[PDB]
Image (cartoon, rainbow, N blue to C red):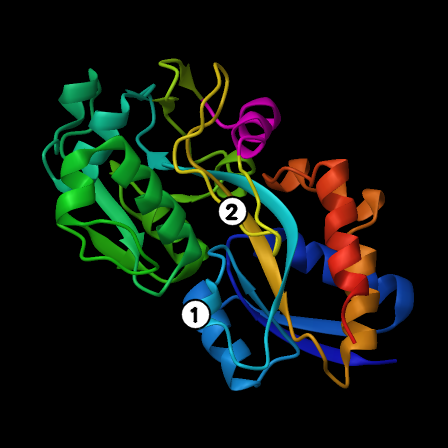
Amino acid sequence: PFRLNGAGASFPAMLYSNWFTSFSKDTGNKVNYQAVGSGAGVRQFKAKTVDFGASDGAVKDSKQPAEGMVHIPMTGGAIVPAYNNPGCDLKMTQTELADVFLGKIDQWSHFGCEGGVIKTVHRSDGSGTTKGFTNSLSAFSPEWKKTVGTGKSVQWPVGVGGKGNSGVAAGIKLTPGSIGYVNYGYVQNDPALEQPALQNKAGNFVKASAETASAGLGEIVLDDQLRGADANPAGANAYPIVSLTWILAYPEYEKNEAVKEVLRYALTPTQQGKADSLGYVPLPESLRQKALAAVESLK
């Protein structure tokens, strides 16, 4: 039996943990995973201190290590504005969401709700979830794009930091009348957090679900390294804040037969089909096949 150690993105960590636990029960092999965020994942990948990395932001050619990297898309999902304000059924335009994170709207009464002051929560660590969320706020709001922009880290006008998707979710839960952003499983599978009906590019107010997240993800056009994003997808029923997420593999590596075994396992329809229960969208069949071919390309 082998051991592997991977690190990176917390966005898919619910699903990766499930897969790795299942793989251990079924095979005896152990695959440990550190949800340190995409920032740290890419750093440790580059430093060769892990068997594989993980990021929700694809790595452009100029930032890839000389020895190369293979992106293997594993899943996708909504990034939602999770909030803690019982009794408030929050509905938000794209401008309003951005204006809440700019500090321009700080009263729950703006949305017709009780709760007093709106407190925001954001990531303290370099984050692919931040990248996606801020990519969307930048598309939603010229003011956001100009004054804050998008990246794994940004300068937040207001709010408190939390570490990982888990720390953001915890901060929202701990602070009455707060809002942040997290992978959807933290909302779907927690009765204390809710999500807003959020305006999409088409003008419809939608909540994240299998239907709306898959609709949004389906608009993403990938390059020949399976990289791509869409900050604000078109379509009547698209959820507007969605991201893919990738495992980062070395093209040639002494333990890649073991890496290949676990990725093949994670890419079966049986493992993939767990995605929805944990707040993710399984790869469409054509992308699953592209992922498997990428896995098989490893040496």
Q: Does residue 23 appear left or right of residue 227 in this picture?
A: right
Q: What percent of the width, then of the height, locates residue 140?
A: 27, 31
**Could you classify mark 1 by the number of other residues whose Cα lies within 10 Å: few (under 14), some (14-19), or many (20 or more)?**
few
Identify the residue shown where x is 22% and y is 54%. 160
Mark 2: few, some, or many residues within 10 Å (few <14, many ≥20)?
some
**Magenta residues (range):** 207-219
Camera-nearest residue between 92 and 174 = 92
The image quarter in which residue 124 lies: bottom left
Is residue 7 found inside the magenta-colored segment of the image?
A: no
The amino acid type found where label 1 is placed reads Ser
Residue 22 seen anywhere in this rendered image of the structure: no
Marking on residue 160: none
Return the residue at label 2: 228
Q: Earlier in the sequence, mark 2 or mark 1?
A: 1
Most prominent secondary structure in the magenta stretch? helix
Between label 2 and label 1, give the one nearer the viewer: 1
Whole-percent x and y of residue 5?
A: 66, 77
In the rendered image, the vertical position of residue 32 relative to residue 197, given as above or below: below
- For the residue labelled by badge 1, is the local secondary structure a helix, a strand or a loop? helix
Where does residue 21 sit, x and y in percent of width and height?
75, 62
Residue in the foreground of this view, choosing between 87 and 63:
63
In the image, what residue occupies the spot 56% across and 25% down?
215
| Quadrant (top left, top right, bottom left, bottom right) of the C terminus | bottom right
What residue does disc 1 label?
Answer: 62
Quadrant of the frame with the N terminus: bottom right
Q: Residue at x 22, y 35 (%)?
A: 98
Q: Is residue 267 left or right of residue 132?
A: right
Inspect this view and state whether residue 177 appears: yes
Query: What amino acid does circle 2 point to?
Result: Gly
Q: CA distance from mark 2 to mark 1?
A: 16 Å
Q: Residue at (34%, 38%) from the top-left corner?
A: 136
Q: Position of residue 138 (x, y in %)?
A: 26, 40
